[PDB]
Length: 505
Length: 49
Image (tube, rainbow over all chains, first blue to last red; front, side, top):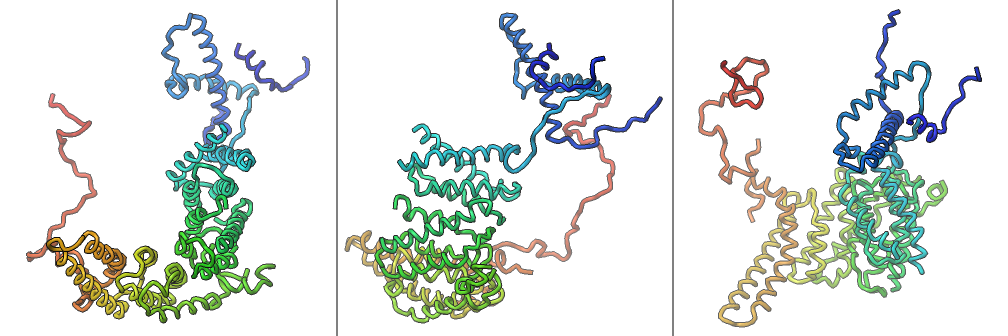
């Protein structure tokens, strides 16, 4: 019955002939077990499973059903199968080894897409994603498929936010591949309108991207140019002034642009379009026909120190001979980059006026110079960051005035309180400025003292007046104190230990 | 080397402060000397038959 079942099932029979003392045996288990041979052997074991289970099912329906406690699935099959069925199997293997017979089956390999099962289901998700976008983009730009796309949104968000270390040790090249294809289908999903939000899913997927350079094969090298053209379109329109092309894209631009450490991709759209996004920010120093910004400083801080994997601007901009045709970057502009930083350096020398009125939009413009161009080659050129830090201290001497902008200034203080070798001890000017901040805190203390003393015996609504004085005193004080307790007491205490004169004030 | 940060103003004390000699500083062996059966052992238990 078994052999006739093979002959009915397997129509694979080969044509062999026409019509008619003590050899020392070596070991046979020296070579490893591949996926193909174990697939074939477990296929023979699975054929034994299916045949014996079909015969058992025939017995079950033959004897009027009846309880069968051996009816347990393949996983909880006891050791009797894996012992005795494999005994009979290997007996058959050594039987067919002699007198010339064998049967072969197989196709598999552990890889980055197909038959490595985690990547198998990741690729199934990517395939269903691309197929679903291909289905739905005409049906977006005019069902059950609406639900069918609603649920894997949350599935991909959960599995990618949960697993982040899947990417960096483990893959051959799908870390670029599947991620960039998912990003491709996200960006063609972008302007096409859906109800449920995905931008957090896109943000965590972008967080999965850094944790190589081969993605011309992927669309991602071209997707960067797509998003740059989108940014130029929308920044020009907003300079003059739409379905989804609004400020919602800037959060994904933030999380994708924020790649300070693992700027791995080479894409090389380096200087032109980022500078093309820079100049609206200076044009947006005034209103200039713009509904009010949302992330001016956050969109400005995306400038890393020429960190598309490593670039540097103004030579291939103004020298298109070998750059655009033939590159001219990462070693050429030893001083060509630093001409506009030197222009920026002069403004803090001028900002001595009190209020936020002279710096309206400078809260977004000043910080990214301090962050990025300082940060590179700090061991080589520390006087630049020193001048920048003391200039920011002088500019926050404007913030020493009691009330400038409680919304912008502490947000920017959190945006850039950083110091490496700039404090009271690196800079005794910073010590005198800390003494000035102590005098400012004494002004706040006298103010709160007068307000509290006036609060006695039902003078006025102290929650409206004395409290509001304390609020406006505390919040910029919270910004300054967060900078202080962040890193001003990072090097002060070692000097206060070594001598007395570090923090006498 | 340091002791200028966290304890000198803060109660924490040098360990061998008021001594005239150091500690013995016991250490760990490598040779396997015999030792009697602890009766508390997980899975090695005897019986004086």
